[PDB]
Length: 123
Length: 122
Ligand SMILES: S=C(NCCc1ccccc1)Nc1cccnc1
Ligand SMILES: S=C(NCCc1ccccc1)Nc1cccnc1
Image 1: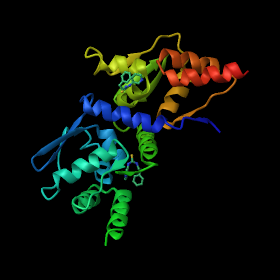
Image 2: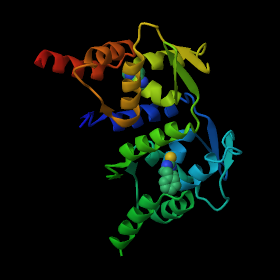
Image 3: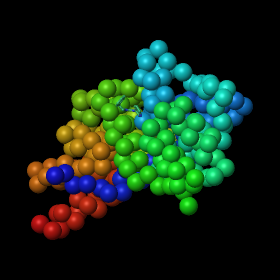
Image 4: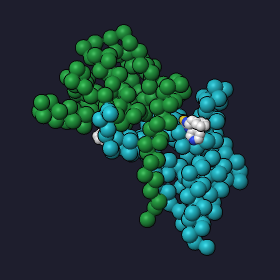
């Protein structure tokens, strides 16, 4: 029965995305084939089961560069990364396959389930 | 156009608080009176105009310890910090004055406005 601020959670994510847009206190580079994506570790492990298992390990917690698998589509990771910071996922008929594969790799089980619904609703 | 996850922002904030509870990637110690509070700077800058101005400054951006004005109540600040990581304010008759004052200091305009509404209602 504490007083709840209905917008506070999304206003924090918005400001966090702004800090990423200005490159303020970002602490890791994600390398996907050729492309590089800078982000905050905390946001990364709060959304992805793979980044969680990487940074939860005290041995890997201080890494500033993560090389994803060479098979991982860079544009798919870019879509999922922007989803982490905005709650808005951009599924298209031309990217659904790459986005879903990337989601399973990053272990984002809710995004994977949504990708299936999108697939089922397009067959 | 894009698919909106209505519970996503809230689930992210919940997982951030879990990281704070286990002290994973906490990167600053906020000291009030003599009590230490461990937090993530990004969460602090996103919720507080004070912590925004502090950590935007390249002189203080990477400091490990920030000491607040000793006029600030610790229990009150603990309530604002908890609200930062949860969206829930433990606003009570016996702490609203301390919570509002601490909110003004941290430059948290929305929490101040909500405090004044409850005072004006009484
Ligand atoms: S921070 C955090 N906490 C969840 C705690 C948990 C860890 C593992 C299993 C259940 C809960 N990240 C996370 C972890 C995993 C997936 N997606 C995000
Ligand atoms: S990240 C951020 N504001 C995003 C950019 C902004 C800077 C200044 C004013 C509005 C927005 N933190 C903040 C700053 C000030 C108050 N409360 C939180």
